[PDB]
Amino acid sequence: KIIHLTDDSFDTDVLKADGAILVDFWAEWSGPSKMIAPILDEIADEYQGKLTVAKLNIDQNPGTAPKYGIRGIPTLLLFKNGEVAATKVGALSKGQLKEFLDANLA
Amino acid sequence: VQLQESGGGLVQAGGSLRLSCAASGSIFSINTMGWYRQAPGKQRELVAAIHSGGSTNYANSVKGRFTISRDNAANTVYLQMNSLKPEDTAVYYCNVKDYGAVLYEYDYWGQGTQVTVSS
Amino acid sequence: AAKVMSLLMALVVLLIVAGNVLVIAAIGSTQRLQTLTNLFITSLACADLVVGLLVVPFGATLVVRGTWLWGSFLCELWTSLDVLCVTASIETLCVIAIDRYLAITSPFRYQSLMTRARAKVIICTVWAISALVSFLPIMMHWWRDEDPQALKCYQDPGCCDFVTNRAYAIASSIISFYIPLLIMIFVYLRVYREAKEQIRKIDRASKRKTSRVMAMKEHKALKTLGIIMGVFTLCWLPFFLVNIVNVFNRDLVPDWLFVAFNWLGYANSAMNPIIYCRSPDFRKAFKRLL
Ligand SMILES: CCCCCCCCCC(=O)N(CCO)C[C@@H](O)[C@@H](O)[C@@H](O)[C@@H](O)CO
Ligand SMILES: CC(C)NC[C@H](O)c1ccc(O)c(O)c1
Ligand code: NA
Image 1: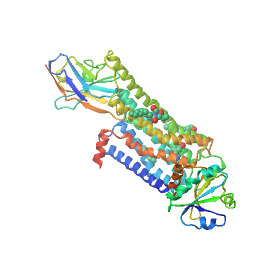
Image 2: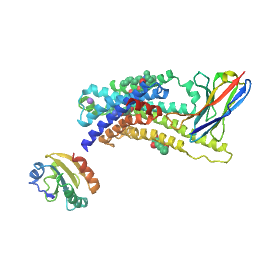
Image 3: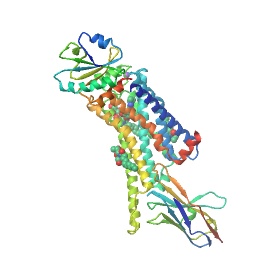
Image 4: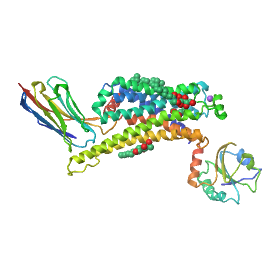
């Protein structure tokens, strides 16, 4: 259920897309960006319907990241009707991350 | 908390009596024990009282004659009544004011014990 | 969670107004409740009630809407009213601790010493000081900082943040919270010491026959004392600690936390009816009113 984003599809897959969408900005070199990868695969199952998880590789698609001002990675932007309602930066555990998500899904 | 009162009865004017109230039960370290009395067809008034820190309080009617004291160990209060008059005739009640709640005081009253003085 | 925050404000207002209205009614309507201690409780309950009726509602809407909807004058007047009622409330908690200290340790002294007229003068003074810390500095702009970004919030009617110079933040916090707290710690510590030393005398009395232990009545006194100091400090120390911090290193503590900690302080006004009105006579009056 994970969307794997590109530079051109971003407008259709996130800004025009239905519901809430959580975007992960990850890189193959970054160890903190790998620690959250298996956690987000589990969240996509448990938060099915409530939100949609998306991943975007910064090495593959460098154009999207400067627009929103991404400094560090991984940085998780929650999207609601093409608008940024929340932000987290760095690696989290499942228990910490669920509490961020449960509170923003109201 | 039960207040057991003794020492009352009949006595001739000019005589002495020694009332004694033992308080069996859970009472806060800081408390005020005293003796009140109620003459026939009158309101209950304070006779004498003693704080747990040695402070005393007497009524002018009984000043110089009556002496209140408390037992050092147990919760027992004595009232030595000397030079008794027929005016002193009343139902003497033992009282404990417990300050364990901090914000308020709790009252304990004994059943009352008759003292009667004749001329 | 954002919807949970708004629900949680509503019950806070309900608890404060309900609780305090009920207390003031109980004291006014019953002849037995009109003691000197309950006179200071009436001062306390008035302050807390004004918090619930005026201060917390307007405060709630500043969180809901993200902005001040009633203009610069009512931001200044509301800020003054907040400080007035919080100052009067916390100072009155301190006066109560002293009242109970005198009535417990020196009850015969207390009766002649603390008259009804003397209690009124004390109450009047608590409110007069609350006014002169709140309305006098805030309305006259003495609380104002010279900083440009601070001066942006004074110019903007939509902005109603609490921004103060160094002097006012210290002085107000001391008068509203720290002087009261230290007096309450000193005062109630001597009630513990008095009760500790009295257990010592009862043990000396026995001639090595018995050693006193903490019974029912001593453990209840410690619990009550723990609730008094614990709840008051839990509710107001965090805000008033931060309120002094923010003057020096401003960015150190976030704005969401500063506001949340202030709301924790408004909750104490809902707790105060519960702590200071548990007497048997209060319990009976409350049953009679409902
Ligand atoms: C019954 C009457 C008792 C005295 C009434 C006056 C006591 C309060 C004195 C006073 O006003 N303050 C403490 C002394 O400053 C608090 C503030 O007024 C002051 O701190 C601020 O005005 C400045 O910090 C602002 O730059
Ligand atoms: C939101 C604002 C108006 N809250 C002020 C706070 O309750 C307060 C009260 C008394 C004070 O002395 C103080 O510094 C701060
Ligand atoms: Na303003």
